[PDB]
Length: 107
Length: 108
Image (cartoon, rainbow over the protein chains, first blue to last red):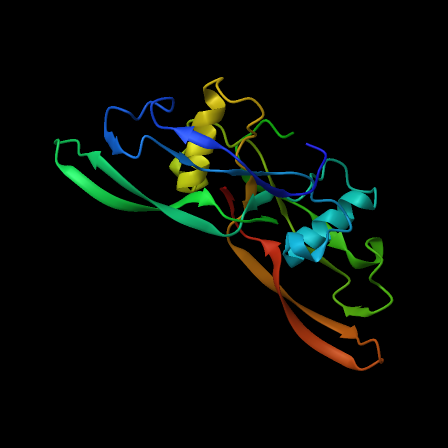
């Protein structure tokens, strides 16, 4: 994945994840994911931590083998409201946190 | 690509080796650490995946949908780093810099 760290479309279908037995609604949801380079020098929009900035320089500046790139990870996220069955077949409505990626950062 | 599970690894950063010795007075180096390792289905609870990472890892495990990477091994807890240094104007400054040292890693 050659481009910079950004958010990418991904639709997750609960039937394809094995969860169609317990989940009533929704059938699917756009989860998105993060991918791309975190390479020296990272643009300020990639919002690197102080650590990721230093890690990126250690990688660029040669020495110290095996130092990976900072990770392209979810920064802002949002919830999903799920209607589903309990282990006991009680119908439950729950807001699950951190379900969909809204933005990505280098960390 | 480290084949072990997501964990914190040793890295000592020397400021002279990253080109910052002109302005940094103390310390001359610090233990930065870094994160690497696998975040694959099924992830142990100790890797503290988010709901999203759990889902991403299942979508990956099932062949369906090409191109989905593993959740990333990133710093969860971090610590800061007091640096004595010279300003652009040659004032001596003491500043605590946040998020300098990895204390723990998570799958995200």
